[PDB]
Amino acid sequence: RIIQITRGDSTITSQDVANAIVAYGVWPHYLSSKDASAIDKPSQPDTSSNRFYTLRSVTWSSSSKGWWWKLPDALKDMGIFGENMFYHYLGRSGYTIHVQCNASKFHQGTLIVALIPEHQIASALHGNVNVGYNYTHPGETGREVKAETRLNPDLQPTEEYWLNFDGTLLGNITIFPHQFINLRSNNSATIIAPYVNAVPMDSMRSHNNWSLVIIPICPLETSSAINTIPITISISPMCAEFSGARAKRQ
Amino acid sequence: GLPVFITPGSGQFLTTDDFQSPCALPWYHPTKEISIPGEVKNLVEICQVDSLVPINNTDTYINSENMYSVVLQSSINAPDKIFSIRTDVASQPLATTLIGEISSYFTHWTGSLRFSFMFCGTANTTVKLLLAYTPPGIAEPTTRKDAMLGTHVIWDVGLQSTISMVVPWISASHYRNTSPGRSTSGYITCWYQTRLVIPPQTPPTARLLCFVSGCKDFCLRMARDTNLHLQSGAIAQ
Amino acid sequence: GLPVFITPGSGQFLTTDDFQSPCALPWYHPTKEISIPGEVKNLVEICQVDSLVPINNTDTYINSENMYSVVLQSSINAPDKIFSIRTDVASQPLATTLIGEISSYFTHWTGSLRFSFMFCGTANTTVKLLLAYTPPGIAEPTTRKDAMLGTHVIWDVGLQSTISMVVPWISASHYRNTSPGRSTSGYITCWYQTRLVIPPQTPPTARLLCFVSGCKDFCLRMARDTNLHLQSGAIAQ
Amino acid sequence: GLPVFITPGSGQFLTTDDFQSPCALPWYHPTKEISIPGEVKNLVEICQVDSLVPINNTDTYINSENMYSVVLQSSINAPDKIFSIRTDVASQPLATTLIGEISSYFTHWTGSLRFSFMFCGTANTTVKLLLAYTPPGIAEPTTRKDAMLGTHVIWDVGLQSTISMVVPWISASHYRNTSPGRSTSGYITCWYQTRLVIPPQTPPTARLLCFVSGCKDFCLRMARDTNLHLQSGAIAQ
Amino acid sequence: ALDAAETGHTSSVQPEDVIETRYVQTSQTRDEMSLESFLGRSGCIHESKLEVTLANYNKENFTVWAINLQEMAQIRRKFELFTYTRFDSEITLVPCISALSQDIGHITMQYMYVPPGAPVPNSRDDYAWQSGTNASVFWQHGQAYPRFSLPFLSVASAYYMFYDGYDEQDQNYGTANTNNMGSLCSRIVTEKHIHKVHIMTRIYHKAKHVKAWCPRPPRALEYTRAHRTNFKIEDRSIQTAIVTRPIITTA
């Protein structure tokens, strides 16, 4: 159960992992002349951006409740990817994602990781409300789930993780392409996806065409004084493309 | 005009009819189907997906992940029962699984079900466990040996993560009704085949997660507007 | 007669239906089609016609030719903005162009637009000018260099009269809605790439006229009774 | 649409109609026909079954088996009548036979009837008996010799259990009406051809049971909702 | 029989592995389970209730409804099962007249599909009832149920069942961005008359020639807010379809 990974300039491994299911079996690819909408020959940064980038350390505990991100927004700051995104009205990209989560032989607990589509998050508050841009687009900073006092609550998404933050049951979440970090089974987990939309390419900053969720399905523990472990995620964009070049987006 | 004469069943609308109809919007043309990933043709591919049972459906766990999970006690020298469930696809809790909901959208079901189980405890830890099924017409078992007379599997918790096993289709009729009223399909039942053994100063605890899906054998009939969900009043906007 | 039975959608009139119908006037015969010039098959040939924008849509020009025209100031050493417009086909003023009206008669549009520009000033006079387009999601530019980052053309005002150029189709969706509500397609924007230079004692002034048409790329869907025009009450006779 | 025009007999429902009709439940599929034993295609196979007449339809026997049976008196030196019946298929008691009921569900009948008779008395006992039929237009016979002028059989009560014989079809018309009002089909009549002889100290008694069925000749027309049975009020549940 | 569910792949697939089976002609068709079945049964969509106002008959007696599949739960849950779906639509109208008066007389009723940027009728006498190209259709007392086939509409390949962002200046998060189909409309066509009446149209649709895109988990709880996935209702709690039991060792 060993893998190595190589994209654009950068490489990844686990020597205790079971291979990704490729999302729907479709290995990532560029747009087709048969399906395209945009007229130009689009921007292929290739190796300089279909390469890995990784998020700030989250860390977790038995008390922890969940984390997620929305893409491409979660990668808006990833140099070439980030600006090439911000300077175009449109683009498209798939992703290779690996989540890094080693423990000792002496830990238990499990996370589910789900790649998830439009994942249209429900409000925290009841009634005539909807989610505000700052929170739907948390950037690489992401959304960890917490017990208390998130301001502007009327525009906040719900914290209700076991309702998938949208009023659907968890545990059926395995309907999406998914994996488990299980500390016995593996030390890491991986998933890869092509581009997807109802449209052949999309307004990157305006719509998170993919999203990624990680949930503490089983509580972290060990008897060791190292009561907590970080998690980090690395992503490479795939076949990344951009079209309608103009100024940098604000 | 041609001499014609009109049969009953004319002039009704049936929400489940089948016919040609004239266009509201002639000369229009739809957008092309780009090759979006995630094709689908039937509900059975959804049935093939393993989904978690909220096995542990009680107050102390319901509003949380923990109703998908059970906790095991390495402290116990006993053969005894860990848990049990029905097997009727639209019974609680199974109905809440996606196969459950799809079955709840239906009136008839057939074919054997896949069940799967991960030893979510500490990697250093060992056990072997009994997962068993009860052919009905009989009470849910009260000794491990009772379940050993049923069809069952003993889990060699090797390096590999998961045991997976099947309730065989043993309905008298080729189908069964998806929801029982005053009726039964049989039981899942779970037991300590050995005691669970952690090595010293490991957490005095373990977790188990449980999965189900339709086997290649599985099928449904009589699609019906599902039991599982209710609308009260108007849906606001 | 043949046993027949009647589907819903019978007995209505739909103003957009499609069918055969019986004749009011059987045995009649129409006049022959003489070869009148000025054939037509589709609206797109009208789209291909360059028509003037009433670019200069203000009080001081509206009731006159002058809203089709802009005035340039050879006195100014500056890089700065001469004018700007939206690009959404049924936005003001563009809607008032014949492509505008045809788009206003429609709900969906696609494909790139042709734009054209004549240096209407004194033949002895020279300049080069920046015509530029802004891909949206962003404010309309406020420096010439901003527009230089957009897709643009610099006009060599040679002997030839006109510069002509295209807003590329850069809609996310293959179509866009013809009229935006709370939505945008991007901007046209125009700037002094050089200063305008007349030779001495020429009029201290110049004129520019601006044209648009559908490119070979252009198309529409969802013909709808146009925004552009209103009837109040009865049309008298 | 095609010019069509509508004949009378349109827009009715006839409980005995014949047509195609649209599906309430499209895309459904029925369960397969397993090879269940006891196939059937027509009512005539039921007609071919011998069923007992409740021959002995009186108060003293009706609420019992005994109305299917007659008792014979070995004490009597006489030629005389043992019993007689009509032959009209829906007359009492014959109507109560299953061929009777099937005929009672019908208005026309044709073809000859099979009749059969077992000497149910003590195995040691002997007799020969006259079973006879009366072609109608005439009274039911009052001497044995009268019946001997009718078509008849004399029963050699050999080792074999049963005599079986036929009322020939002698209707003027190819059919007859299934129930007579003021009408007749003829009589069955039965007589001591010899005296019955038991050997000494045998029971001073014997029994006879009587059967009927449709011959290969038999058929019916004008299926009608049967005379034989009544519903009063609502059928409770 | 052993696997790693953590792979994401479905578990040890085969039933013959752990039962010493007899051969059986397992021969039950999945065709009712097809999408052209499950989506392809009609259901109600919306409720066009109106009162015939007298005092300005000419003004008030029309309605308009924003087209969505998001406010009748059963149909909603068919489509709230995917990222995207595409279909042609049987549309069926069940017009009903309810009398507040001793009779109804003859009555005739208009409907119009109002695609966005058609001029919306403001009045039961609005020139917008003229419809040179808008799909407008008529019903009257004693007429059979109207129906039409509406082809797949979207500017995109498929309808968004969900969306993860905004119209470009950042409000209306989700389907309220993407799903601008415009509106259906209805209006009494008979002129002013003495009968106080309510007209109610139940409107139905079946998706056929269907296609669907990446399944997603079913709705667990009551709906709330059409376009929005909101579910935490006011002065209420999250009583899902899951039901509790006293102990997990008791079935």
Image (tube, coloured by chain):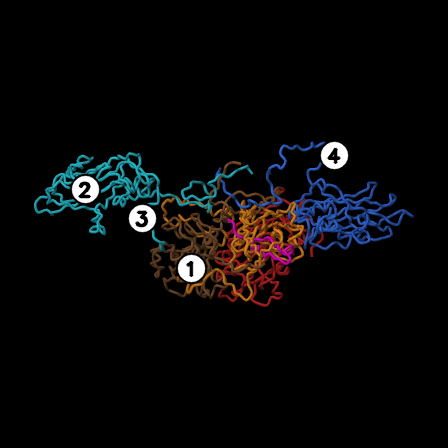
Chain colours: A red, B brown, C blue, D cyan, E orange
- D207 and E197: which one is in front? E197
Q: Which mark is residue D229?
A: 3
Which amino acid does the dot numbered 4 rest on?
A: Pro
Question: Badge 2: how crowded within 10 Å, few (<14), some, or many (20+)?
Answer: some
Of badges 1 and 3, the one in the foreground is 3
**Quadrant in the rendering for residue E123:** bottom right
Q: Which residue is mark 4?
A: C37
State yes or no: discs 4 and 3 in contact (Cβ < 8 Å).
no
**In screen coordinates, is D131 left or right of E55?**
left
Q: Chain of mark 4?
A: C
State yes or no: discs 3 and 2 in contact (Cβ < 8 Å).
no
- A166 and C108: which one is in front? C108
Q: Is residue E48 magenta?
A: yes
Which amino acid does the dot numbered 1 rest on?
A: Thr
Instruction: Relative to E155, say whether A123 is above or below.
Output: below
- D69 and B136: which one is in front? D69
Please provide percent x and percent y for residue E200. 56, 54
Q: Which residue is mark 2?
A: D118
Q: Are marks 1 and 3 on the same chain?
A: no
Disc 4 from disc 2: Cα separation:
108 Å
Q: Which mark is residue B126?
A: 1
Which amino acid does the dot numbered 2 rest on?
A: Met
Q: Chain of mark 3?
A: D
Which amino acid does the dot numbered 3 rest on?
A: His
Q: Which residues are magenta?
A: E41-70
Q: Is residue C149 visible?
A: no
